[PDB]
Image 1 (cartoon, protein in one colour):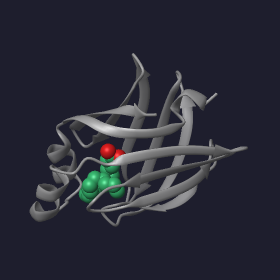
Image 2 (tube, protein in one colour):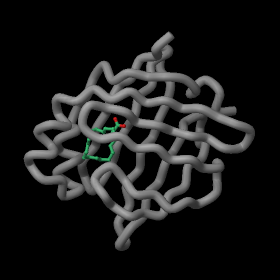
Image 3 (cartoon, helix red, strand yellow):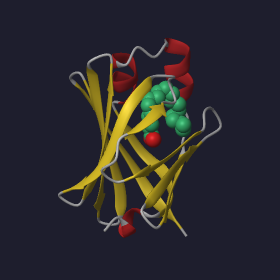
Length: 133
Ligand SMILES: CCCCCCCCCCCCCCCCCCC(=O)O
């Protein structure tokens, strides 16, 4: 059910990422480098387990999870969160919870592009990834 999300994806558009990072309390120097970074996201499955890698010249992350099962995560900005990823309306919805705060990372496919929408507080960031062969 997750299969069209699988593969290697490269960042090709970013809107409001600084707003999102600011909302999370990321410092100006980190936001500055991040605003010029173009990550590669790799999504793989092995049975029920998904692994999502995010690689860049600045920071790298990797998570593994089962859909619908909570997991601990330490984010790129060093938040220790409780996470769950589900399919909802054909979108891959990742919810992170910490200190009573929530942020969502929603992925959807539009015309073969991967659109990642990041919401925290009032900040809404939209990042577009295109598929590597
Ligand atoms: C780890 C790969 C590099 C992520 C970009 C540069 C580093 C940002 C650090 C500070 C904000 C981190 C916010 C949470 C993760 C955003 C994930 C956004 C995406 O997958 O496109």
